[PDB]
Every structure is written in structure tokens, then in C-alpha cells.
Length: 280
Length: 262
Ligand SMILES: NC(=O)c1ccc[n+]([C@@H]2O[C@H](COP(=O)([O-])OP(=O)(O)OC[C@H]3O[C@@H](n4cnc5c(N)ncnc54)[C@H](OP(=O)(O)O)[C@@H]3O)[C@@H](O)[C@H]2O)c1
Ligand SMILES: NC(=O)c1ccc[n+]([C@@H]2O[C@H](COP(=O)([O-])OP(=O)(O)OC[C@H]3O[C@@H](n4cnc5c(N)ncnc54)[C@H](OP(=O)(O)O)[C@@H]3O)[C@@H](O)[C@H]2O)c1
Ligand SMILES: CO[C@]12C[C@@H]3C[C@H](C1)[C@@](CC(=O)N1CC(O)C1)(c1ccc(F)cc1)[C@@H](C3)C2
Ligand SMILES: CO[C@]12C[C@@H]3C[C@H](C1)[C@@](CC(=O)N1CC(O)C1)(c1ccc(F)cc1)[C@@H](C3)C2
Image 1 (tube, each protein chain N blue to C red):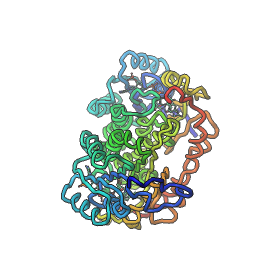
Image 2 (image 1 turned 45 degrees about the vertical axis):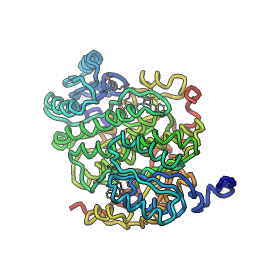
Image 3 (image 1 turned 120 degrees about the vertical axis):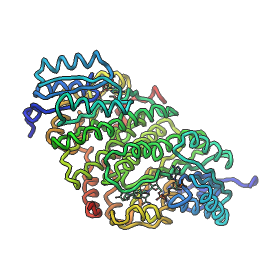
Image 4 (image 1 turned 60 degrees about the vertical axis):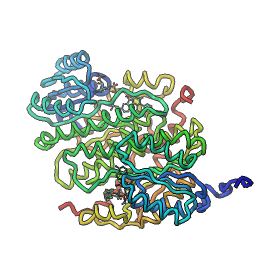
């Protein structure tokens, strides 16, 4: 270890993933007691990463930590709390960073509990969705950025197809997912001109076979679900490869149509329409 | 094809109407002979607007001053505006919290305030307005930006709030379609407009072609009156060519046969 040095990232490392890219990496996974988050903790553990998992339930988080250690995690810890509390979110990153002695990857995955319902007057669900699904991600990013700058790290943002296109019955949820794209795609452009070597990966997911999703869709929505294990891995890969966006859906037609080439062209056209020297 | 007659005698709310695009919309509506209720925080600028609206030919013109940071004011404002006009045909959501071009570092207060004013108040105003708009088979007009469709640096909080509007209003538009709620939703995607606020904020940063505020204000009204889902208004021909997302419309139509609704 003290007599060891070098790098895993060389020729083709921006295109071809290897589990060794995560060996010894310091990773935070939010909403990691169940679903996709837990699957990501498990994949990272198998890759020999140091992990700090979070969710509200300490009991479910203990089980994830124990299984992570069994799978071969370099180290595994949990810190339980609610992402409704901006003080907890801020404190959580400092404590997770202290446990690992730094941070390489921040995986933002938690959401507030949501169901399929038509919008009528539930402004409280709209506000809570914005607070938990979006604002806490911004707070976690602010708290994590100094450590990420030090490691030339990665931010992984778990979004949804409902964060790129419109679906009925998910108005509050969809607003919070669209907000993530607007926020994180803007700071990615800022990091580029400011030479902040921190990658940002927005993950656009279709229906995933998590217990929460399968229960919420039941009898309302009839779509093909994709497996949570492969989903979790595809998210990690995108983050390790520093890809701007990850798309994961069971339909081949979705993967074919989801990309927005015109958005990328437009953004390139505007890159020379603004003088930024004053901020850089 | 739009006709100014489409707005004659219509009951319209215009938010952030003390200046810029909002004031220009109030003026166009006044000339078309609509009943208008304008809002912003500045009493003295709203009074001037009301006066000029009356000189232009408005059926009636009123103002109610207050901050859209206050969700209670937003909710009560619609009830009082509706009482003044005896109903509501069009709700024009245009106000934003004061914003400047800056890199994002740690101003969570500006992120939260932008979400509250630019987005959450629009939802509160829509909830308060919907019973009257259902009665008139009315219209909701949402003023967004190109920063609400594509990424730009220095506007992270602002852009997140504009993207949130697209996600929220495009979802409820699908719900209104299947629920047979005859209330149209127009999302307006604007480029640089020659308002005093924008010209002052982009000074030394953006020179470019700034689209005139008067034509902008009319194009928003037209889209709303024509019940168009989206309005695009920019000075660049390349923008109008690339801004549309036909693949998004195709995907949404493909998923349309995946829901029950009953
Ligand atoms: N599954 C799908 O179909 C699907 C589709 C598209 C996108 N996605 C995205 O994928 C991510 C994971 O989804 P999932 O289906 O895996 O969810 P899930 O199985 O329901 O897990 C949600 C996680 O977040 C935690 N959580 C809930 N409320 C919280 C709060 N207030 N504060 C902190 N943590 C909280 C939960 O544990 P506690 O309750 O113990 O806190 C749990 O660990 C989400 O961002 C979701 O939007 C999922
Ligand atoms: N100008 C552009 O280049 C441009 C480009 C794209 C999109 N847009 C969109 O166009 C719309 C109008 O922009 P504009 O350029 O015309 O802006 P503007 O001239 O600065 O006017 C903003 C309006 O909002 C009001 N307002 C500000 N803070 C408020 C608060 N807390 N509560 C209630 N009202 C508040 C202002 O009045 P008070 O200060 O008196 O309250 C004013 O009437 C916005 O939605 C903006 O995003 C503009
Ligand atoms: C994790 O919790 C859930 C709770 C609700 C059901 C389900 C799981 C999901 C998944 C999701 O994000 N997408 C699949 C769509 O492809 C987008 C959904 C399901 C079908 C939709 F049409 C829209 C939204 C949202 C809303 C998030
Ligand atoms: C009304 O207040 C303003 C204050 C700030 C400057 C200016 C006017 C605007 C206008 C705007 O939304 N767009 C023009 C772009 O075409 C989108 C802007 C300017 C240059 C950008 F690169 C991005 C955003 C935002 C942010 C809104």
C-alpha cells in the first residue's frame, strides 16, 4: 500500500468500465436502505469501495452495512436521518467524509415517498418533493464539493424519464426531477469554464422493479419494469466513466428517442454568446 | 390565426406586471378591451400601469400589490382579482424573484427563494384560479425561458425553477386532457428580451440581438388565446430551429397507452 502507486484510468478508461475503477474509492449512497440505492451499495461493496449509506431507518441501514462488509467492502458505515432536515444533510457529508478520510463519489438517490395521483391541491406534497428530491441534493453537493475538488471526484444524480418528458399523475415528482436537470446541468457548464474537475452524472431511469415502484404502479400504470440490480450497476458505471447522462429503460424505443441532440447543439451555439471572464 | 377580438371583454390576471414583459402584456390586453388585474410588490408602478391600461381602452383595470414569497397573499390575490372581475378567463404567470448572473457556490437561500417565487407561487396561483378557469374553459399562461429547456451557466437556481415549471405544468396538462378539464396550459420559452432588468443584468456579459419586449408580450398573449401548448420567442433563427423537441412528443404519445385513468 505505502510501496504502491499508479492509476486505473488510462487508454479506453473513458469508454470501458472495470469494477477495479471503484476499488478503494470513498462513496456516499443516499436512500440506500432499499431499492436501487441498496443495490448500488452492494455493487460498490463487491468492487472493494469504502461506503457510507444513509436513509431514515437505522435498522434497515444496519442490514445493508453488514451485507456490504460480507461482500468485500473496504469499509462500510451508516448515518441515519431525514433529508427533510437541511442541517442533517449538511452534517451527514462532513461526518461521512471524516469516516472515510475523504470523498470520491456522491450518489444522490433518495426521494420523499410519492404515489400516482392526479394533482388537485396538495401544495404540501409539491413543497416536500422540492425540499427532499431537489433542495437536499443541492445542500449535499455544497457540503461535498471541497472534498470532491480534492479528489477530482464525481456527483451522481438519480433522476427519471419523468425528469425529461411529461407524464400525468406525477406533477410534483416530475417538477422536482426536471429541477435537478436544470440545476446540475447549469453547474456542470460552470465547472467546465472554472476548471473544477468534478463530473456530474444525471441518470434518466424508466420503471425499475423496486418494491416501492411495483406497489405504486399496481392497477394504474401498465409498463415493463427493468431489473434493479442492472439499473444500480449502470448508474455506478456512468459515474465512474464520468458520463454526463445515463439512460436506463426496458424499452429499446425509449433509449432510441430519449436523447436530445438539438439541446446539445443549442448549448454549443450559446457557449460563445456570453462573456464569463468576470466570474472565472 | 389570432384576432385581438379574442381578448375583448376577457377577465385576465397578469403577475409581475409593474414593469418589463408583464407591463407590455397588460398594455396589449388593455388595447384589446380586456378586464385586467395586475400584480407586483410596487404600488406606485402598478398605479401607473393601471392608468395607462385605462387610457389604452381596457374594459376595467385594477391592481393588488404584494409579494409572491407569501403563499397566503398568492392564494387570496386570485380570489380578490376574481371578485373584482366577476370571474377569470386567463391567468398569466410571469413574475420572478430578483436574479443576477453569478456562478453557484453556496447561496442555498437564492435556490430556495427562486423555487418559492418562480415555481411554488405559480402552483398556488393555479390551485386558487382553477375553479373559475374551469367555469370559463379558460387558460393558464406560464412564462418560462430558454434556460427552462437547455442548460446555461450562471443561472443554476433560476434554471432549476424554470425546468420545474415545465415538469409540473406539462404533467397537469396531460391530466387535464384525460380528465376532460377544458383549461389550456401555455408554456412560453423566451430568449433575451430588451427589458430594463435583463439589459442591466447582461451588461458586459451578453451584447447580442435582444428581442423587443412589445412583440414578446403579444406573442405570449396570442399563444394563450390560441391555446397552444408552447410558445417560442427568440431573435436567433437557429434557436427557433433547434428549441423544439419532437422526440419528447413522440415518447409521450407512445406512453399514452400505459395508463388506466378510471
Ligand atoms: N423504481 C423506479 O421505478 C424508479 C424509476 C425512475 C427513477 N427512480 C429514482 O431512483 C431513486 C431510487 O428509487 P427506489 O425505487 O429505489 O426507491 P425506494 O426503494 O423507495 O427507496 C427510497 C430510499 O430513500 C429513503 N428515504 C425515503 N424518504 C427519505 C427521507 N425523507 N430522507 C432520507 N431518505 C429517505 C428510503 O429509506 P427510509 O424510508 O428509511 O428513509 C429508501 O432508502 C429515486 O431517486 C427515484 O426517483 C426510480
Ligand atoms: N427579459 C428577458 O430577457 C427574459 C428572458 C427569458 C425569460 N424571461 C421571463 O419573462 C418574465 C418577465 O421578465 P422581465 O424581464 O419582464 O422582468 P422584470 O421587468 O424585471 O419584471 C419582473 C416583475 O416581477 C415582479 N416581482 C419581483 N419580485 C416579486 C415578488 N417577490 N413578488 C411578486 N412580484 C415580484 C416585479 O415587480 P416588483 O419588483 O415591483 O415586485 C416585476 O413586475 C419572467 O418570468 C422571466 O423569467 C425574461
Ligand atoms: C420510486 O417511486 C415512484 C413512485 C411513483 C411510481 C413510480 C415509482 C414512478 C417511477 C418513475 O419515476 N418513472 C417510470 C416512468 O418511466 C418515470 C413512475 C411510474 C410510472 C410513471 F408513468 C411515472 C412515474 C415514480 C412515481 C416514482
Ligand atoms: C428577467 O431576469 C433575467 C435575470 C438574469 C439575466 C436575464 C434576465 C436572463 C434572461 C433569460 O432567462 N434568458 C436569456 C437566455 O436566452 C434565457 C438570462 C440572461 C442570459 C443567460 F445566459 C441566461 C439567462 C435571466 C437571468 C432572467
